Amino acid sequence: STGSATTTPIDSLDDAYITPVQIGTPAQTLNLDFDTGSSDLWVFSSETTASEVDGQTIYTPSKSTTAKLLSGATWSISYGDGSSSSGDVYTDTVSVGGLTVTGQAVESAKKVSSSFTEDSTIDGLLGLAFSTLNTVSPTQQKTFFDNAKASLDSPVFTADLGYHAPGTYNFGFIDTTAYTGSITYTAVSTKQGFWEWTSTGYAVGSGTFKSTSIDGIADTGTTLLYLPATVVSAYWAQVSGAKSSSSVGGYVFPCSATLPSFTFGVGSARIVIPGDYIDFGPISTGSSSCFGGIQSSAGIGINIFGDVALKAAFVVFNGATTPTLGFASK
Image 1: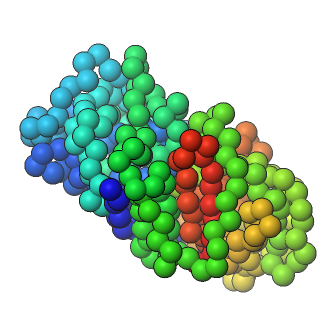
Image 2: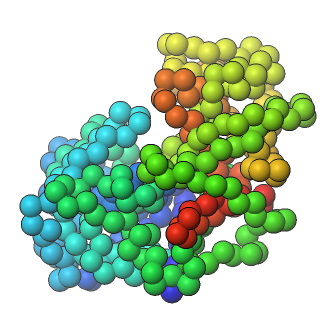
């Protein structure tokens, strides 16, 4: 089997991407944030505290003939941005782009933090990291991809995120029309539960490539590119007037600037992020200070190849017995 679903930016900045997901019988379609940095499929629901729902579409398990309470199971998750959610668990039929999993754990939110409430466009998350990170207790649950894997034509999914445009998540096949050149594959460590890999270096603009190992994670659920402070300083030094602002929370630059590209290495291959992809617009409405799309990871504990980086590439998440990642230009 295979599946193919379009993913759409939630706003004009590509702050996140939503993908429609069918849950239950008859289908209830929710728009979920596919997150290769976490491993829980959770939704706003009929159980979510009413004051914490503001415009989201909810899953109502009582209206699904295939929903079954997973008795005793609870979940609770905190994300790197400080957001969180928690609740109980149902199993139900879940379909993405024509690919159907029966018995998928659907984690129903009883509580969500303010950032989820305040984003009316995201009805929940669909985790695509390794199932060892799943938070369901006392019986850990498998991700949608892990449940679908055995049925897929090939044990892979691909992320093809658009810049200010829709893109595609495919399951079970590699669309050879969706990229240029060849796909370069690179090793993955699953020891932290992430799609963790080592980039071979970077370049700023037309500058020379610096060969250096940068361990990080491929994370579709993070907006920006978070890299070591040395790398990020070298980038922003090429933008007149750019500075790190403790009050804003990162590097800002004059909105009048033209940003240089940023290149990252995948083995001997190179992925070029155009400068425009690094512009996240005014820090506040009407400001002439703009927020940068490359930021320091120094306070995180891990480097994160988020959407800014991934949207410059066609990315293969290879879930074979030894997982790997593939990157191609497009």
